[PDB]
Image: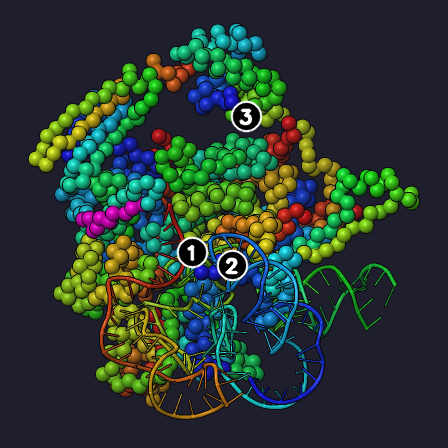
Amino acid sequence: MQNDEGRIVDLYIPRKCSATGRLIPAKEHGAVQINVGQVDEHGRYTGEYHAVAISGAVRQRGESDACLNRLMHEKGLLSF
Amino acid sequence: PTKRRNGGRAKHGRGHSAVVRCSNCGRSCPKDKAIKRFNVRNIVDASSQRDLREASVYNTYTLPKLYIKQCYCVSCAIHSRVVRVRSVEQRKVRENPQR
Amino acid sequence: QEDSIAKMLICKAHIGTKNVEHKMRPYVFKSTSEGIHLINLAKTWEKILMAARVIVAIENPADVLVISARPYGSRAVLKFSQYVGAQAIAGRWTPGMLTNQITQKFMEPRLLIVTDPRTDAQAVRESAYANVPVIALCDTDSPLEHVDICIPCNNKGKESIALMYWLLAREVLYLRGELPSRSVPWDVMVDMFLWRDP
Amino acid sequence: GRVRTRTVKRAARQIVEKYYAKLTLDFQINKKISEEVAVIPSKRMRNRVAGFVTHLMKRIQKGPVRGISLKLQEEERERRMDFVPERSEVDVATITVDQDTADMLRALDINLPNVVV
Amino acid sequence: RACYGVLRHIMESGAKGCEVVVSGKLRAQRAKSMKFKDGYLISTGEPSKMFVDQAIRSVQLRQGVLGVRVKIMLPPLPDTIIVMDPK
Amino acid sequence: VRMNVLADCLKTLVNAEKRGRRQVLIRPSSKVIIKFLQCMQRRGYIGDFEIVDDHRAGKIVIELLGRINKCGVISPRFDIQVDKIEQFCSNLLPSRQFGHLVLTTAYGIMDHEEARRKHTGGKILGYFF
Amino acid sequence: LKDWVPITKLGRLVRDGKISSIEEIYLFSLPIKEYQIIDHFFQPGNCAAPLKDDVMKIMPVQKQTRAGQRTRFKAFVAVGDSNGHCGLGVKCAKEVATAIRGAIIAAKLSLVPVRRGYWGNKIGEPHTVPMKVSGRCGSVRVRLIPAPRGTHIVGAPTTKKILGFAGIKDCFSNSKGSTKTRGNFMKALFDALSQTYGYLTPELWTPTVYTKSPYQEWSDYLART
RNA sequence: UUAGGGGCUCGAAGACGAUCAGAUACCGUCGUAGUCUUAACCAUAAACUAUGCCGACUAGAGAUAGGAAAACGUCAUGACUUCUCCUGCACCUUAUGAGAAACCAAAGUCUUUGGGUUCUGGGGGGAGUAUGGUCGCAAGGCUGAAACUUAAAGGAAUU
């Protein structure tokens, strides 16, 4: 949301749910943000991670986990 | 408003069911909506039947049971306390009490 | 590696119920005669490797909960609270933990873990008021609604619950760096996680 | 009836938590004991709480009682919690599989020592 | 505004609880008794007469007389039992 | 029975959009739909799509993103006169800034933004935003 | 007045002054449970500007029980600071002033940010509902439409106030259904404005950054009591 | 209802006997038309799923009726078990889908408003009345007003 020349007007940007790509509003208290930690060789290790967020619209279906598998198959660390 | 989704008659894809007369009232109700208790029972109670086991001819005898199918009117049932009446939540259950 | 999959046979963790949910169906395979369904034991252990990496990457481990209504969880969960330094509840949950600030058992966790989402559904309902991601040990019966990250096992067997909470604690510890090498299996036995009759 | 209110319950229940030592199953020492440890204003109330203290001590004698912190059981509950045998698994090498359960690993791979009963 | 100010002083002073009733007509021709209460206040028994203190006055206005009650619970009760810790 | 082919497919699309599917198949497919989907695809509202060549009307399978709030159809296909493209989208579209009317014209199927600068109206077909 | 003892993770962080402003809370979608959190951000003079509260309506409600009737008063209160922040709250109580206290507390707790747009050309601070946004509550449909600058607000007097407390300068209101029930009408108007951020434009097609939460970055403070 | 058959039982009318202040009713005992059938009429019922008819897409589980395919399946062309497919009457669970709510896989996909089409409604009475028309052997059916009247009728839930 720009105007005239630069200056991103408005306050903040709503997070976009990974599973549906649909924006999470202010008062969705059923929203989630997972952190999943990486590992080095013979790890061990955390602190570097893949963040991922999903809305309460997706969760109350029961389709949270099936989509969250897809979002960490493409990263590498599952093999479904 | 609909007090029952069913309507209490339990009829689907007919347009016309069979009819039965109530065993007490007299009333023509539909067979589906009748409310029926098939009362099997032996003839001489339980306490009184030992007289027949004492008195009788033959070494043992099975006292043969009386088989009747009662059919009721709703109004005859609720008066006679076969069904009485239930809450809005507990209405929906269709199982057997006294299996 | 192979040995966790070998131990899952001794658990009877591959066994589940007659009825199977639509969501839980992918894990189950080759339903047996008698109408009992079997779980892919690769797909169980791959999701403990998932679920360990979620629990690690939390700074304070006390912000994790572990919950169980059923009494087979009670000795299991209270040993889990030692090694991963987490809060723990057993028995009756008392709703308005996560809502209701005034109540003196007001806990505001980041992550939440459950045995069965069927038996303590009231915990899993309350997670959706406070932005708390769940983890669950699912059976083929149990629902996935407000459940992130299933770990599909036998829930009802008293052996089988322990031998998940053994593998998580062990899995979490290696990630944590608590265990220096993977030549040793572990110091502590399985049988600290169990349940006894008296 | 002689049902006791929560003010009568709480006081008698709190005594056996912490002052469990001392008082015996006997009543007439407990009537005296209750008064000294804690304030009780009236004479009728001191018997009614002390009767319920001896009722709890009988129930503690009979079995383990719910709702009492005492912690003696915990000290002794933790000794049950502490104990462990040799092992309930890796026992012994081969595991009693079935027709269906063995054919998981034949499809899935992972080689192991197995049985087919 | 007046009755809260009187109720605030006795609560600040270190009374355990209180109430203040005002009967009689008020913004109306029919009578309508307003009631104000904060902190617990027993009504019954011999422990009423000691541990409460209670008072009543008249007060006279253009349209009629108002009532005014006050009742104030004070700080060895019958009901409460304070049990010691042994160490 | 089945009068508008385009009208069925956009309801099929917008349902399985709101449910939140990765990809959907539609049927029976046509020359109009691929051209209607092509002018969504320029503006960046859906990804790729295949069109299986079964020996029949055919099935169109689209990859899609979480981007279309809605697409619809205006039966009857009204005529509009370049003056009156501005009057329609004031009524129809959610704002003046974003969204598209889309309308068949003798220089091909196109958006109302393209129909203004080519300077030719035609029959209105549908919309999306 | 007064030094409240913060309860919960959010309460502790705000008093210390670790979280900067409420857009950080609204991003990660965290429930604000005490009103003392939101009292902190809107400080007098400092706030620019302080939150303003107006009492929309007072309605007497009666329950017929046994002998006599008991009447309680239900107080609708909207509250907002012009510049995109608005709220809507209700409470009932036996006296009138005791309802309005708790109504203002509930209004602050249900405080929602409102994005705002330009109607065509886009120069010099936004002034409108950015698209045609509907809201419903209980057979009251309300539809807010962008208007050109200087249009002002077109709508019911009730409509002017709670769009006024958002900061929306220009509108065209429509209103189907029974607008007589002001309890439903305010909720319908309010839940329209709540959905403004929820609606996805081509301006927000770019994939998100994912910053750390305020729960994450100030975890080590929340270890100690 | 009309004209022939048949007429057991039940039974609008009618008859007495009870009950009651009265009781032309409930209850009881008789009992003609009718009930049944061939040949014409009549054309309405809470004729109800009080939800028009085709079409697309939305969500699962277990039953069930009909047909079809598979299994070294179990017992003797068929019965049963396990599994999939369409086509039926439904049922349970749930919804960031809808609704005023009751409730609803349709009453969903509708202010983010347009797949095709038939019929009907516009506060409550007056009134389904009056008059005219037309169908009917009649009973009545279909079509169908006004003067005057009135601030509420009506729906779903709560105490």
Q: Residue at x 44, y 71 (%)?
A: F13
Residue tagged 3: D66
Q: Is residue D22 magenta?
A: no
The reply to whether residue C95 is in sight is yes
Q: Is residue C128 above or below residue E56?
A: below
Marks 1/3: CA distance?
Answer: 43 Å
Residue tagged 2: B4
Q: Mark 1 lies on which chain?
A: A
Looking at the rendering, the stretch of residues picked out in magenta corresponds to G54-63
Q: Looking at the rendering, which quadrant does residue H107 occupy? A: bottom left
Q: How crowded is mark 3: few (under 14 residues within 10 Å), some or many (20 or more)?
A: few
In the picture, measured across the screen, residue D101 lies left or right of residue H153, that is right
Q: Which of marks 1 and 3 is in front?
A: 3
Q: Residue at x 28, y 66 (%)?
A: G176
Tell me where residue H132 appears, x and y as whole percent.
35, 91
Give the main secondary structure, helix, strand or loop, of the magenta stretch.
strand
The reply to whether dot 1 and dot 3 touch (C-beta < 8 Å) is no
Tell me where residue A13 appears, x and y as whole percent.
30, 55
Q: Residue at x 47, y 42 (%)?
A: C123
Residue tagged 1: A57
The residue nearer to you, when weighing G71 against A55, is G71
